[PDB]
Amino acid sequence: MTGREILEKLERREFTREVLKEALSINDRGFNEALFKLADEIRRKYVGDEVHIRAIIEFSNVCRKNCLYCGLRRDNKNLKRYRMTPEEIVERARLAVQFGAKTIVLQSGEDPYXMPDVISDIVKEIKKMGVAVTLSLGEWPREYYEKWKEAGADRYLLRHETANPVLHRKLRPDTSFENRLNCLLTLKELGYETGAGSMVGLPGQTIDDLVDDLLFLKEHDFDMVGIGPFIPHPDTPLANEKKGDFTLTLKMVALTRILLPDSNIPATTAMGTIVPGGREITLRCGANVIMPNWTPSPYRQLYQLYPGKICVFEKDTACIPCVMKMIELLGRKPGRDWGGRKRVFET
Ligand SMILES: Nc1ncnc2c1ncn2[C@@H]1O[C@H](CSCC[C@H](N)C(=O)O)[C@@H](O)[C@H]1O
Ligand code: SF4
Ligand SMILES: [Br-]
Ligand SMILES: [Br-]
Ligand SMILES: [Br-]
Ligand SMILES: [Br-]
Ligand SMILES: [Br-]
Figure 1 (cartoon, rainbow, N blue to C red):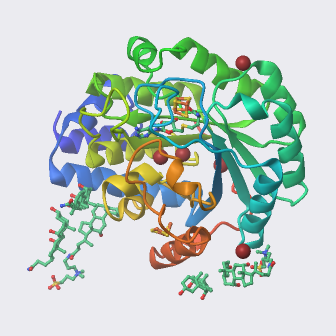
Figure 2: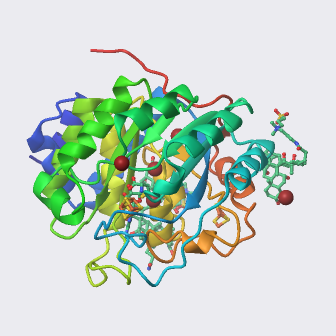
């Protein structure tokens, strides 16, 4: 098909494997710009001009897993490890709420120390502040997820990473795609607003794999989808592999908006790391959420999933005001409520 014909099929919601493959394979500038415009319009029509701010506290970089792409992998001995205390985490969340955050995101490596009860205690304290709580702690037993839901957690982010089970097992040797999916299904069953998503440009990953990611997201109708480029980290086995392409990753965000028009989709920090102004671009191509870094000094620079992460050298209260300025200069508005998914039922 020509670019014009693929756009017309996307506009009529004929989301076949062939249409998605062709959309990802065409490199024409006119086609790409029209795809980005379509996603931007679908975003405005379905989720409006509000950009929801999720203040993220990366509270521990301790991890038991050995994911091949990740700087926090347990075999990385060249990383200073840290843990915030429960009191530090609560008080830091309180500061974010004082600065206007309406969602607090707690993210960490898979650090057993806190699980499950210290997390439960922390969640209960933050929920007293009248904001949404989102967890991003990795793979744990159903019983842990249940306890956190009972403690008041609202949402859980657990990117599926790659929907190719063979590639998944190789990159994430402690676990499997089956396990990841079982975790996501359990979270949904428990009533969490659930987030999935993937990296783009992983070693071994093909365009067909990317199409399968899109199809997987459509199949499960996730509330949130987090997408970023793979960024090689020098203290990992993938150090010499090629970085993910920004434009290809941007096309994955645009298609995700087109496929899931009422979902919440972040402009991820990885997008801002690989291209200056990458998050702003992404907010104009389908994204409607941003997650300013609220990890306190002196730990920001130690949370090194990937190198060169933006904002790590700044005073640690910088990013909430910064994203508020960003939202304004984009001609957008800040979120007025917790920014939960507002489903638009259709055919
Ligand atoms: N090198 C890298 N490049 C880009 N993104 C990466 C990365 N290493 C990790 N990430 C992303 O960072 C996300 C958060 S990892 C921290 C949360 C939890 N330990 C978990 O694994 O879910 C991952 O889901 C992954 O997509
Ligand atoms: S991606 Fe998550 S689980 Fe895997 S090594 Fe990094 S922090 Fe640990
Ligand atoms: Br302070
Ligand atoms: Br969230
Ligand atoms: Br366990
Ligand atoms: Br995300
Ligand atoms: Br990211």
